[PDB]
Length: 158
Length: 158
Ligand SMILES: CCCCCCCC/C=C\CCCCCCCC(=O)O
Ligand SMILES: CCCCCCCC/C=C\CCCCCCCC(=O)O
Image (tube, rainbow over all chains, first blue to last red; front, top):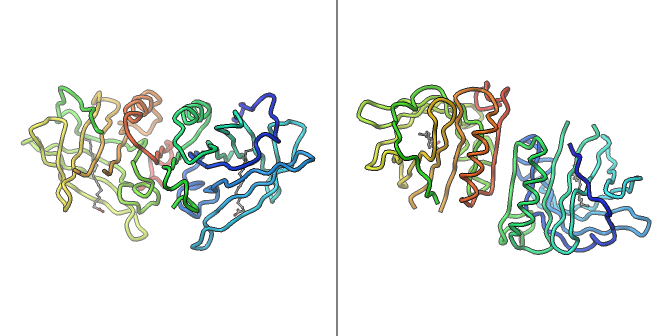
């Protein structure tokens, strides 16, 4: 929890478009409603030249699908990034083939936890979903969501 | 969908106390919020002497955890029951050992679908959860919830 990170990660190679195909969290309230705190839909990853990672996403806030831009700073571990605000909050990359799928988790350091299966394409990748499910049997997840290709082409999935 | 029913079911032997340990549905909106349509927490099963099955449950309605009593009428198939209202709505018993776990699904006949893993006890039965997960890989589920022992002893899980 979480003791699965990607060895040999080249962060530059994750740049580009991603779809949040499936989400899971340790507590139901983290993903329950459209405005739940960790219900965030990844749009694009943009690594900076110094190795930080800026993230474009959508979040439902106040009855509307809002755009967000957040910055995840590099640490000494290539697969681990930190986000300010307030509580120390780390992003861990568990696995990726760069070209098709990426699995990551977000945990508050230090209890609470959310993971996603990102895919390059608005398609149900059964095989990325299988790897996501395997990575999660090691974790105490209590809500799990997945989306279909129609919803994946909509803002806030929708 | 759903093509898994329990052979040899003795409905009388499912009477008694049950806990809704985990829930899954084909559409996110079926389980999303506390007031979602299929977010129902089983309390007790009471088979009638003629083989019908009355169900006591809780549902969050209008900012409160309400008690419900619904009747599921027997069909020609021992593992399949029907509920009036409005849309023909069947309950199917997939598997049970009577003493520990029961898996069932509710489907609108005929599209939409929700399944639960019921347990006799406010304990996480990993082995019933495994069987639930196996029964579901055959199904198009897009939301899955589970509850911990604390929540299981609360009204509306809570
Ligand atoms: C390298 C894998 C990609 C990682 C993408 C990480 C996703 C974004 C991480 C955390 C977002 C947490 C929710 C914050 C939403 C913005 C502020 C808020 O509304 O609370
Ligand atoms: C034999 C296995 C036990 C089956 C228990 C079935 C659970 C109850 C079945 C369907 C309930 C569907 C929701 C209806 C809630 C009451 C009316 C409403 O608020 O819409």
